């Protein structure tokens, strides 16, 4: 043999798979290098061939139950090829799920938001909305883009996401899994290994445990950013409350990188920018790439394949030639390692070269593994490798020895605090975001969060874990999570969390081998074979061994530790604590940007009706919002003589309770930013209170408009 | 009922102290921020009236409760 | 020739006469655009309740779906209900009459009127 | 109405429907949607236009813009 026949099968499979895979990869490389319809067909046909081939081999693998298989190598390859996947779903189920996935992706990519001022001017997220969320400092403009993105596209995804969840769970359950969340936690799962075994549930525990150890540092970062944002947005942020979600420097608040302009610790101090030195010393793309190669060779990593240098888009075509330009390492196969990128004479491009080449080095190292066992130990191993490369290369030390930063300069601790904060805005800023998002998805997939509480718990978790508050209350007609790419495009997210940890663990371990004496934030692993050796040990492993074992290969551990991450930001932490001495380190999950003008309303049907007391449903609520809108119109047209067309949609309801108590506020007919002041709303209610009471067969006593009273 | 925003009619004469006990279990801190007058009925019965109060206060008030209050 | 009276929506159009002086008389409110807005909103409410209960269907009928026409100083007008986002889908008068009958009391309460003052021509109070 | 991402301009799409389509519902959609969107936007502009135009004509010795 069973194992013998299984091994024989895998052997034959691998021989054909590697070759056909190469053809597909080469075809894709060609089309990426030259965007042509002919090339489209080439890559498409090649991809179809490999996919069909893999499917047939998948069934053949099923004919070899891994239970009888004792050899781990064959067992691992069998298990990987064996995986049925969505194929377990019925034809109708599979087709529907695929349609939902395409619809969701299309809505995300083609969804548009029109300016309320001019309906003709409509912005897409990718270019316009992102620019506003990353550059605009207008509270109103940022609020518009944030809410409009969720109000237009988020609703379109709500029903699709619901079906998606159902079908996804079915498929995974049929693939022997508790839920789609468990299906996704299978990546980090290790079995039949002595001490290197790891449960899918273990991941959850580990993530949560590690997260609790980072909370302190993040709280200080949050408090510091809040203080600075209070200056940028006065009369908008509570010094003890959460942070408005539309002010985090992007559409979702994934990264806080765009908040640096408003949070620079030492404005007077700049940061290292050797792009000028590069251009001054005529640093072409090839030169910068050689520097990358030099660095790797310095740490004792194999020389870049001559083939790489031969076939690799290392610079923009510039001519009629049309080629995509995203930095990407290519393992075309059969010893083919290429890099495609529109490289320029920039410090960023220099570091990107190191990052991309880092992936190539990993590929080359595991290229000698079984075709199916040629990949990073887990989904967070490969990216971490690239990251630690850029880390060591960015160090002013490295640049001063790369001949870009005159070593006569002296690195200022202020510029170090500057650098550390900028990194924290990208690294520490995404950790709660990533944690909370995966947590929500996991609970949703396992059913812990019901459909009627999807948005409810989303914002509860946001306010508690991330310390971020919604500027506008979002009911279960919204799907805020689905408005993010990964969610709408069926991608796991815990990779990002785990990678971050792994990256710092790797960096520290390697620097210990490099015999670093200073702050880890300024460590250059260049010129250290020992660091390279440890790195290589894991690098060459691939998927052959458990990720827990590969960890022990470099860091020596089997699980993700956050200590090294904290160690890296320790200087910043100490500094932040000083700045947050006077400030309140923490947030209250009660303050909201709309609570100030929110009117609490308690309703007593049974008090005024007893028997024949109708059940307050959404229809009753719809009626209420309509009644309030009516009141607002009357008040404005009478007191202000202003014909303002207030609709039930302008009436924003929140904190609905079984007491039939809720907080509500009124906005301008087409202006989320323009919140009608509570004073005016109170007057409007007073004016039409009787009418509203009549509509619900209630009275001032039963229809308690807290803050409004009879006289 | 207002403190925990519970559905109207859930708390009765029977499920009241136990209700607030389970309610304190949920909100122990808030439970201490809620005044609660003491109801006895016997204490109400054992409250002495002021002189002439019985006729021009007790009876007068009871009649207001009675229907066709002017008749009585 | 042609009749300037025939209308493609007249068939499902329900005439409504409002008698403020007959009911409220003194202290009667003035029927304005806001009163008409409340009326369309009230009809939308009724339509939602009818479909949610009798048809067990969640249809988000809005004041916009309530199409009002031939408005008169006697506060008379013909209205027809349409699908939330489908102008072509006009709710049959029969279904609308059922919804009206179901929520007539609440509609009357909303305008402080009565079946006599609030006349839904064709919808007969019992 | 089905897919909000698919939007038609008057000449490119609406005209083709109003000229070729024989579906009552499709023709009704395009006709009403054209007047429920562009038409509503022009209402206020046209009201001012008529005023300024009348002003200019009367200033040029005319009963109204139509005169
Ligand atoms: C992947 O698909 C195969 C084939 O349907 C599944 O193997 C079947 O398992 C059931 C339950 O033990 C048996 O009754 C069938 O006879 C098996 N079929 C074959 C061809 O062996 C396999 O269990 C599926 N794997 C997952 C995880 O769902
Ligand atoms: C388990 O199977 C793998 C794969 O066949 C074996 O790895 C082979 O080891 C021999 C001897 O070193 C090499 O010549 C082959 O090239 C290896 N194959 C691959 C694909 O790596 C492994 O030795 C087996 N283990 C046991 C205990 O039999
Ligand atoms: C690591 O090794 C490299 C290669 O020897 C060193 O690169 C030198 O950098 C200095 C300063 O820019 C130059 O003057 C030399 O000419 C470089 N040598 C070569 C061969 O390129 C680098 O400085 C070393 N780093 C450390 C920290 O020792
Ligand atoms: C960088 O180091 C200098 C020197 O230690 C720091 O300047 C000191 O700041 C403290 C606090 O204000 C003073 O008590 C010292 O007298 C200062 N020393 C000197 C020589 O001026 C500076 O604050 C540090 N910067 C950062 C970012 O921590
Ligand atoms: C929508 O409402 C917001 C909030 O009222 C308006 O923002 C105001 O803009 C004026 C003019 O720049 C400022 O003086 C106010 O301080 C702003 N208020 C706030 C709270 O930011 C915005 O202009 C409105 N937009 C439109 C089109 O009317
Ligand atoms: C919108 O409503 C109209 C009217 O009900 C629908 O058009 C009808 O569609 C059915 C099914 O094809 C036909 O049998 C009817 O004859 C049609 N009526 C008319 C007046 O043509 C239309 O399908 C609805 N659109 C959507 C998107 O649901
Ligand atoms: C166009 O402009 C000319 C110049 O203002 C007008 O001619 C004048 O008319 C007034 C009224 O009869 C006289 O008082 C001026 O002396 C004239 N000016 C000149 C330079 O001759 C002419 O009437 C205007 N036309 C229209 C249609 O408004």
Image (tube, coloured by chain):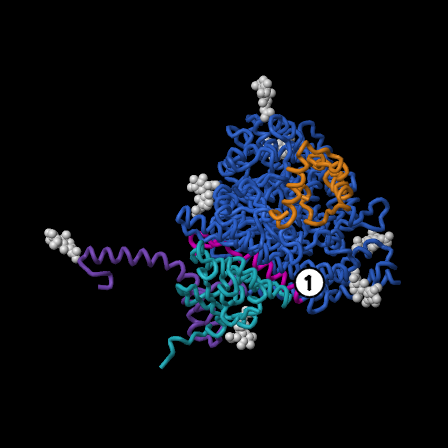
Chain colours: A blue, B orange, C cyan, D purple
The residue nearer to you, when weighing A107 against D57, is D57
Residue A45 in which image quadrant: bottom right
Residue A55 in which image quadrant: bottom right
Residue positioned 76% across, 55% down in the render: A370
Residue A458 drawn above or below residue A88: above
Q: Position of residue A193 (x, y in %)?
A: 84, 48
- Ligand 2 is found in the corner quadrant, namely bottom right
What is the chain identity of the residue bearing mark 1? A
Cβ of disc 1 within 8 Å of ligand 2? no
Q: Which residue is mark 1?
A: A20
| Residue A392 appears left or right of A512 | left
Residue A199 in sight: yes
Q: Identify the element where label 1 is drawn.
A: helix
Crowd around label 1: few <14 · some 14–19 · many ≥20 (10 Å): many
The residue nearer to you, when weighing B35 against A475, is B35
The span picked out in magenta is A95-122
Residue A500 drawn above or below residue C66: above
The residue nearer to you, when weighing C32 against A666, is C32
Q: Position of residue A114 (x, y in %)?
A: 47, 54
Q: Position of residue D55 (x, y in %)?
A: 24, 55
The residue nearer to you, when weighing A587 against A247, is A587
| Residue A613 appears left or right of A264 | right
Residue A287 in sight: no
Q: Position of residue A502 (x, y in %)?
A: 71, 41
- Was residue D18 drawn as part of the magenta stretch in this picture? no
- Was residue A114 drawn as part of the magenta stretch in this picture? yes
Q: Quadrant of the N terminus of chain C?
A: bottom left
Query: Given the current orientation, which residue lies at the most extreme bottom position?
Result: C1
Q: Quadrant of the C terminus of chain C?
A: bottom right
């Amino acid at each position: 043999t069973i194992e013998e026949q299984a091994k024989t099968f895998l052997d034959k499979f691998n021989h054909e798979a590697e070759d056909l895979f190469y053809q597909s990869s080469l075809a894709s490389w060609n089309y990426n290098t030259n965007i042509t319809e002919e090339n489209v067909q080439n890559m498409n046909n090649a991809g179809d061939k490999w996919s069909a081939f893999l499917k047939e081999q998948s069934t053949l693998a099923q004919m070899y139950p891994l239970q009888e298989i004792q050899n781990l190598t064959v067992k691992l390859q069998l298990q990987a090829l064996q995986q049925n996947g969505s194929s377990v779903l019925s034809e109708d189920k599979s087709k529907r799920l695929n349609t939902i996935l395409n619809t969701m992706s299309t809505i995300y990519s083609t969804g548009k938001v029109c300016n309320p001022d001019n309906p003709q001017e409509c912005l897409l997220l990718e270019p316009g909305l992102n620019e506003i969320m990353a550059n605009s400092l207008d509270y109103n403009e940022r609020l518009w883009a944030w809410e409009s993105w969720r109000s237009e596209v988020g609703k379109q995804l709500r029903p699709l996401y619901e079906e998606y969840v159902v079908l996804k769970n079915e498929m995974a359950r049929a693939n022997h899994y508790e839920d789609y969340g468990d299906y996704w936690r299978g990546d980090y799962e290790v079995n039949g290994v002595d001490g290197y075994d790891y449960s899918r549930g273990q991941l959850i525990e580990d993530v949560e445990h590690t997260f609790e150890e980072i909370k302190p540092l993040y709280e200080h970062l949050h408090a510091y950013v809040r203080a600075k944002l209070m200056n940028a947005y006065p009369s908008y942020i509570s010094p003890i409350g959460c942070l408005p979600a539309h002010l985090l420097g992007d559409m979702w608040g994934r990264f806080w990188t765009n908040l640096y302009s408003l949070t620079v610790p030492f404005g007077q101090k700049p940061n290292i920018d050797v792009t000028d030195a590069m251009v001054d010393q005529a640093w072409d793309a090839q030169r910068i790439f050689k520097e990358a190669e030099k660095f790797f060779v310095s740490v004792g990593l194999p020389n870049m394949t001559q083939g790489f240098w031969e076939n690799s888009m290392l610079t923009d075509p510039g001519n009629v030639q049309k080629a995509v330009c995203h930095p990407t390492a290519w393992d075309l196969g059969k010893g083919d390692f290429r890099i495609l990128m529109c490289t320029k004479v920039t410090m960023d491009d220099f570091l990107t070269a190191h990052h991309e080449m880092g992936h190539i080095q990993y590929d080359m190292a595991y290229a000698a593994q079984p075709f199916l066992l040629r990949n990073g130990a887990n989904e967070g191993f490969h990216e971490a490798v690239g990251e630690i490369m850029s880390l060591s290369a960015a160090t002013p030390k490295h640049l001063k020895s790369i001949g870009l930063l005159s070593p006569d300069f002296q690195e200022d601790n202020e510029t170090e605090i500057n650098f550390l904060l900028k990194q924290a805005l990208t690294i520490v800023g995404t950790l709660p975001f990533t944690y909370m998002l995966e947590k929500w998805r996991w609970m949703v997939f396992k059913g812990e969060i019901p459909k009627d509480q999807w948005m409810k718990k989303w914002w509860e978790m946001k306010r508690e874990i991330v310390g971020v508050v919604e500027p506008v209350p979002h009911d279960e007609t919204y799907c805020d999570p689905a408005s993010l790419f990964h969610v709408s495009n069926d991608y796991s997210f815990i990779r990002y969390y785990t990678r971050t940890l792994y990256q710092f663990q790797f960096q520290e371990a390697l620097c210990q081998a490099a015999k670093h004496e200073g702050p880890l934030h300024k460590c250059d692993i260049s010129n250290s074979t020992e660091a390279g050796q440890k790195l290589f040990n894991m690098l060459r492993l691939g998927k052959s061994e458990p990720w827990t074992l590969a960890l022990e290969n470099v860091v020596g551990a089997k699980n993700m530790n956050v200590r090294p991450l904290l160690n890296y930001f320790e200087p910043l932490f100490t500094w932040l604590k000083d700045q947050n001495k006077n400030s309140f380190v923490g947030w209250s999950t009660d303050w909201s940007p709309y609570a100030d003008q929110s009117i609490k309303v308690r309703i007593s049907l049974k008090s005024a009706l007893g028997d024949k007391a109708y059940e307050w449903n959404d229809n009753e609520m719809y009626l209420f919002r309509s009644s309030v809108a009516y009141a607002m119109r009357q008040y404005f047209l009478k007191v202000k003589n202003q014909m303002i067309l207030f609709g039930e949609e302008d009436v924003r309801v929140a904190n609905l309770k079984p007491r039939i108590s809720f907080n509500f506020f009124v906005t301008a007919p087409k202006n989320v930013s323009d919140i009608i002041p509570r004073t005016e709303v109170e007057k409007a209610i007073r004016m039409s209170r009787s009418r509203i009471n009549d509509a619900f067969r209630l009275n001032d006593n039963s229809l308690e408009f807290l803050g409004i009273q009879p006289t | 009922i207002n403190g925990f925003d519970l559905p109207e009619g859930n708390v009765t004469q029977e499920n009241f102290v136990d209700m607030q006990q389970r309610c304190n279990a949920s909100d122990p801190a808030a439970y201490a921020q809620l005044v609660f007058q003491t109801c006895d009925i016997n204490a109400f019965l054992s409250e002495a009236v002021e002189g002439t109060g019985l006729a021009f206060i007790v009876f007068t008030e009871a009649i207001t409760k009675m229907p066709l209050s002017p008749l009585w």
